[PDB]
Amino acid sequence: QIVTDNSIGNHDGYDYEFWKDSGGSGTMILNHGGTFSAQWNNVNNILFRKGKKFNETQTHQQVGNMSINYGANFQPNGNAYLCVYGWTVDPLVEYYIVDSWGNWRPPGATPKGTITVDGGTYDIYETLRVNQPSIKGIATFKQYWSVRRSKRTSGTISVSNHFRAWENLGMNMGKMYEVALTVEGYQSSGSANVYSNTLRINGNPL
Ligand SMILES: *[C@H]1OC[C@@H](O[C@@H]2OC[C@@H](O)[C@H](O)[C@H]2O)[C@H](O)[C@H]1F
């Protein structure tokens, strides 16, 4: 259950993944249920996550309501995100619902709107990745974002409400590929202890 290089699998019912590009190091310890700890040092880009991977046949509406209850001790030293993250396919989209960050509030673009949900206010953004790594090879794809206006590191994220807001703004979504509580680091070091992470689909825990 010690993961220090790229790996995808299932641990205690959750689909976990460790992903990094070259350089630096990271360690992910897979703990009970959706929980895990992460540490990273001198990386270029690293992501640690536990959630659900899907078989690319259903819209978010067809999967049903997705909600994540979480808590994490988030200790970045530099740039990092604490978020819900995942992908759709057809179209290929990477997405983020960011509740906390390190020194830099992402994603550096002009907001397209705002959503109020889960006691917070989130700015909504759309950015572009050109010829970058993806779940479907080197690709050009949009990134969709909801970013909280102030940081928090525990609570509930009503994922499907974000998806409805994005679609209302014309941020087209494809078939679900993944939804997961994620820690991302960029050109930084840090640690995170995700001590609570429960994904419920239609009110039922994974
Ligand atoms: C958002 O997160 C990092 C990266 O996505 C990874 O692409 C490679 C794939 O194997 C992993 O599962 C993904 O996390 C993407 O370039 C970036 F936009």
Image: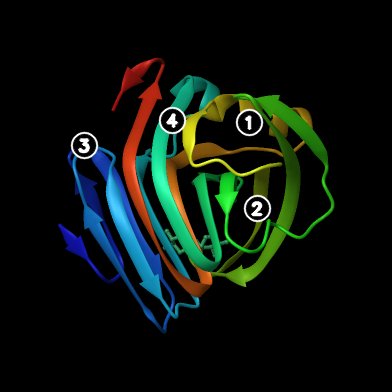
Of the two numbered discs 3 and 2 on the same chain, state the one appearing first in sequence.
3
10 Å crowding of disc 4: few (<14), some (14-19), many (20+)? many
Question: How many marks are shown on the rendered structure?
Answer: 4
Please tell me which residue lies in front, 23 or 126: 23
Of the two numbered discs 2 and 4 on the same chain, state the one appearing first in sequence.
4
Residue 198, position as x, y percentages in the image: 34, 31
Mark 2–mark 4 Cα distance, whole angstroms, equals 20 Å
Give the residue number, with chain letter if any, for mark 4: 68
Give the residue number, with chain letter if any, for mark 1: 162
10 Å crowding of disc 2: few (<14), some (14-19), many (20+)? some
Q: Is residue 117 left or right of residue 34?
A: right
Mark 1–mark 2 Cα distance, whole angstroms, equals 14 Å
Give the residue number, with chain letter if any, for mark 2: 143
Image height check: is 60 above or below 10? above
Residue 192, position as x, y percentages in the image: 38, 56
Quarter of the rendering containing residue 130: bottom right
Of the two numbered discs 1 and 3 on the same chain, state the one appearing first in sequence.
3
| Circle 3/circle 2 CB separation < 8 Å | no
Please tell me which residue lies in front, 1 or 89: 1
- Which amino acid is tagged 2? Gln
Of the two numbered discs 4 and 3 on the same chain, state the one appearing first in sequence.
3
Of the two numbered discs 1 and 2 on the same chain, state the one appearing first in sequence.
2
Give the residue number, with chain letter if any, for mark 3: 13
- Which amino acid is tagged 3? Gly
Residue 25, position as x, y percentages in the image: 34, 77
Q: Secondary structure at mark 1?
A: helix
Of the two numbered discs 1 and 4 on the same chain, state the one appearing first in sequence.
4
Query: Which residue shows up at 61% across the image and 44% down it?
Result: 151
